[PDB]
Amino acid sequence: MGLPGRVPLWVILLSAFAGLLLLMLLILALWKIGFFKRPLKKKMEK
């Protein structure tokens, strides 16, 4: 066994799709660490 090192066009899709998962998770991950860093309209009643 051993491929000639070919590069399947899918590599771009399979990769782009693979990296998308992390690339998204970072953006979403921040949001959790972001939104959470912004409490909604504090309470009142003094």
Image: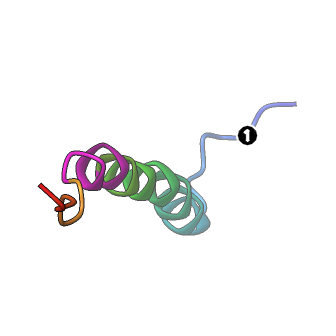
Q: Which one is in front, 19 or 1?
A: 19
Any magenta on residue 37? yes
The three-letter code of the residue at mark 1 reads Leu
What residue did someone put label 1 on?
3
- Which quadrant does the N terminus fall into? top right
Other-residue count near label 1 (Cα within 10 Å), few / some / many at <14 / 14–19 / ≥20: few
Look at the image and say whether residue 40 sits in the magenta stretch: no
Magenta part of the protein: which range?
31-38
Name the dominant secondary structure of the magenta segment.
Answer: helix
- Count of picture labels: 1
Name, please, the residue furthest toward the front. Answer: 45
In the image: residue 34, left or right of residue 5:
left
Q: Residue at x 38, y 53 (%)?
A: 23
Please tell me which residue lies in front, 35 or 14.
Answer: 35
Left or right of residue 32: residue 34: left
Between 10 and 20, the residue placed more toward the observer is 20
Among the 4 quarters of the image, the one containing residue 4: top right
